[PDB]
Length: 152
Ligand code: HEM
Image (cartoon, rainbow, N blue to C red):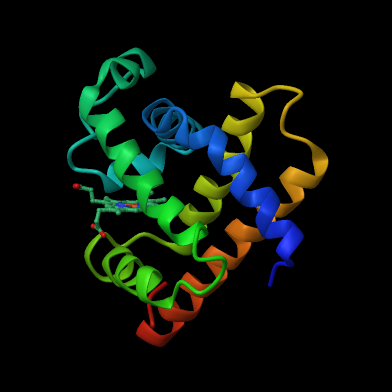
């Protein structure tokens, strides 16, 4: 649950992402894959990537980064009223991709890391607080659907 002022911070930060969605999406996935190499094994189309240089050179990884952040941005713009947008993603990630909630924690922290890396000194403590709360809400509502499905 976020206040109006917190949502305003989230959507202000998101403007930074929308200026370069592919570059942000690429770096988020690279941070996930290099920090948590077990996550790469869930992607049949990226498991061939052995080095970060190959990851950086992969145009399909940048494409998928655009898909991921476009979906997340659509959810964030609903300011919590995201049941219709979130349900299909919860279902596909639990039942088809088999993504444990832990990996959603990993990618949430990766987003925070990338924002500081690309905007050092321009991602203030209030903005980090609000973005963190928004990603916690996203993860918590996914977790509720995971529990319904019995997925661990
Ligand atoms: C912010 C969190 C995430 C968002 C918004 C997101 C979004 C998406 C979307 C929109 C798709 C394509 C449609 C679909 O299959 O539902 C997708 C596919 C997929 N996601 Fe995610 N995802 C997220 C996190 C993760 C994480 C953490 C993992 C694994 C560590 C993951 C694994 C996958 C896989 C394996 C696919 C299929 C890729 C393919 O072969 O095309 N997702 N995701």
